[PDB]
Amino acid sequence: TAQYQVQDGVAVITLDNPPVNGLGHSTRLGIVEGMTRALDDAAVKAIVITGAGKAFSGGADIREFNTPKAMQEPTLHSVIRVLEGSSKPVVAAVHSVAMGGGLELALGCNYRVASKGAQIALPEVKLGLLPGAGGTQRLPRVIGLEAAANMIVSGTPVLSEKFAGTKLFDEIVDGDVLPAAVKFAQNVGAATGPHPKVRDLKVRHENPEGYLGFARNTVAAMAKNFPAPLKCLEAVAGSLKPFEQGLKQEREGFLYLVTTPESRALRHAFFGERAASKIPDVPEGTPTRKIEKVAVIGAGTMGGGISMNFLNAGIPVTILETKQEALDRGVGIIRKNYENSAKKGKLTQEKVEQRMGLLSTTLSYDDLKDADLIIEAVFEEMGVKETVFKKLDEVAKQGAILASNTSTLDVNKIASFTKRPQDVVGMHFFSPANVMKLLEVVRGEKTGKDVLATVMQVGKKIKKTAVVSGVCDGFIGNRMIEQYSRQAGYLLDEGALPEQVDKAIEKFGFAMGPFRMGDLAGNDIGWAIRKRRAVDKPEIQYSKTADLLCEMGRFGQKTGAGWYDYKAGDRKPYPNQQVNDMIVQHSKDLGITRRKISDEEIVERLVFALVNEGARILEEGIASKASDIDMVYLTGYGFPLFRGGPMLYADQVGLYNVALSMKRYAKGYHGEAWQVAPLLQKLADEGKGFNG
Ligand SMILES: NC(=O)c1ccc[n+]([C@@H]2O[C@H](COP(=O)([O-])OP(=O)(O)OC[C@H]3O[C@@H](n4cnc5c(N)ncnc54)[C@H](O)[C@@H]3O)[C@@H](O)[C@H]2O)c1
């Protein structure tokens, strides 16, 4: 809504829709109703528009995105139209935040006055759109083409006081904006003659094609599969035309971006991060335990990684090791990670020391006595875990939460080594744990709901995207990546080589293909894993190619040699002759006439195996919703942000067509991998998606 108050011949319209005065329907209507009242009232000679609380306005109200109310009139286009055609002069009084539609509204007013320290932005590019209510046209008219292009392409905020000597603000003040804006309004409302409009100004620039040519290149190079940034630049270029043409060209830009799958993807990512925290049977308002101090068992790469997340947030950690060398080795790796980030400009050295100052080291379980959360990050062997969870079940205070960073061991079994299984939980971080955003939270059968609520809240405090998975081999991410890695192997049998598969799937948009990834993880890890599949009650086949590779001791980057070769301090993975002859021999030995596999088939086989298994995961309820699987693959596996995740991608492709492709692959090599998940078949039969 909008408050309306007359004071001293000035109507003040005050946007009020916390937390950021989102321009929702009721607020938009409110601004117009107020303007109607103001023009009607003879005593009112000028108008001030401002915002309550901690914003002028942060733009579109996100709680309206998917509603009709988003587009219900008056729209922002209609509101602005009302402000520009106002016979009485309109002064925007900006403070704190003026972003997106909020800036656009301010630019629609005759005059603008700001206080210092206000954040100014058009961030629409971050959602794959562009400023669609005149921003691309009015902004370059008040700050010039280059400054405007830069704000709009990048979406980055800029403090109000940095616009001194542009026309954006007619007066920049210290102190409160409103008093100064009312005084401003009083003067202008006592002159007549008509009042200026941003649309009458002209973008003056002495070589547009000079600049735009260079901007085109740098934007194209940085933009990489996102079409919004170039369209924003194009829209801004239109500010050189007469206002109405520019605006028509902007609207077309907007409507084109709105159709693109890339902005569908960014929107899915944005809302998926928010929906990740929702668990079907744990309602908001379920109360959480206070987590003030943390302990970690293990100072290896994970343990040291996990710890840094808590330190970065200001939460003290106590790392426990067996030996004083493993400790002082880990603490040194932590410190080397930080001082290093500091040289790349990610932190000051001061910040490094305040972080290291929150880290404690012990060799003894008695120091973990007042830790609210303890995270086990030790070797993957049930025997060792049993030792740690027994020692922890003695010491840990009553109410502490005990978590395992296991990625392969049964969380429920680790829990029954204690007499408080309701307090045990998976917290599966992803290597490197201080950079990868993904936290997989594994809910045990016994895990209490209060424990789950707490872990999610913690997740948020350490800036992870935390997704709840039930218990099964590989949880959500690894269970899916196994099916993907199986198709990769099978593609080698049939006629692919590692570099070929990696390059195809990297061009599709993965950060790193299956072979490069296995080389980075350590190919032996997977070797260990598969060897307890044929042991345990399954007989799922894999291509023997990865076994063979490991029988040569080509374990990856750690041995200097995996599917490729690696030379020191050199980023390139070099294709290896011994590996590629092994792959070609193996095909010879299997009876297979190797053939030419298309990049399209590589991608389809790999990505559709993620989708098939994701569909079984949803049917089993190991993930509560499809957007969570997507969030796992964006934040854990380097699935391209521009496609939104495997499950959104399959919907974009169309489930009916994904199903058909699968039935064709059911007839080729290892056809049993391509039976169609029943949930996928059913959604395909009914013309629905996983997401919508
Ligand atoms: N499930 C997985 O495969 C997976 C996934 C992520 C992390 N993790 C575990 O976290 C580790 C991080 O690095 P790392 O193992 O290379 O070296 P690490 O140093 O973290 O391995 C565990 C450390 O804990 C210590 N340790 C072993 N047993 C212990 C016990 N009973 N009590 C106390 N301390 C003990 C050892 O000094 C060892 O250095 C991972 O590498 C892995 O072992 C496992």
Image: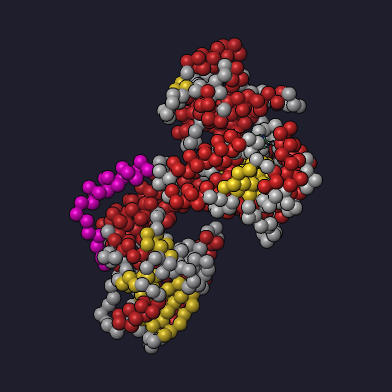
Magenta segment includes 183: no
Task: Please say whether residue 441 is visible from this viewpoint.
Answer: no
Q: Nearer the viewer, residue 617 or 635?
A: 635
Seen in the image, is 173 located left or right of residue 526? left
**Majority secondary structure of the magenta segment?**
helix
**As drawn, which residue projects farthest toward the right?**
419
Name the residue at 52% across, 39% down: 332
Q: Nearer the viewer, residue 4 or 248?
A: 4
Seen in the image, is 665 located left or right of residue 173? right
Q: Quadrant of ligand 1?
A: top right
Name the residue at 42% across, 50% down: 348
Q: On screen, 690 above or below 82?
A: above
The percent coordinates of residue 265 (x first, y second) are: 50, 47
The percent coordinates of residue 218 (x first, y second) are: 32, 44
The percent coordinates of residue 636 (x first, y second) are: 56, 40
Look at the image and give the residue range highlighted in magenta: 199-222
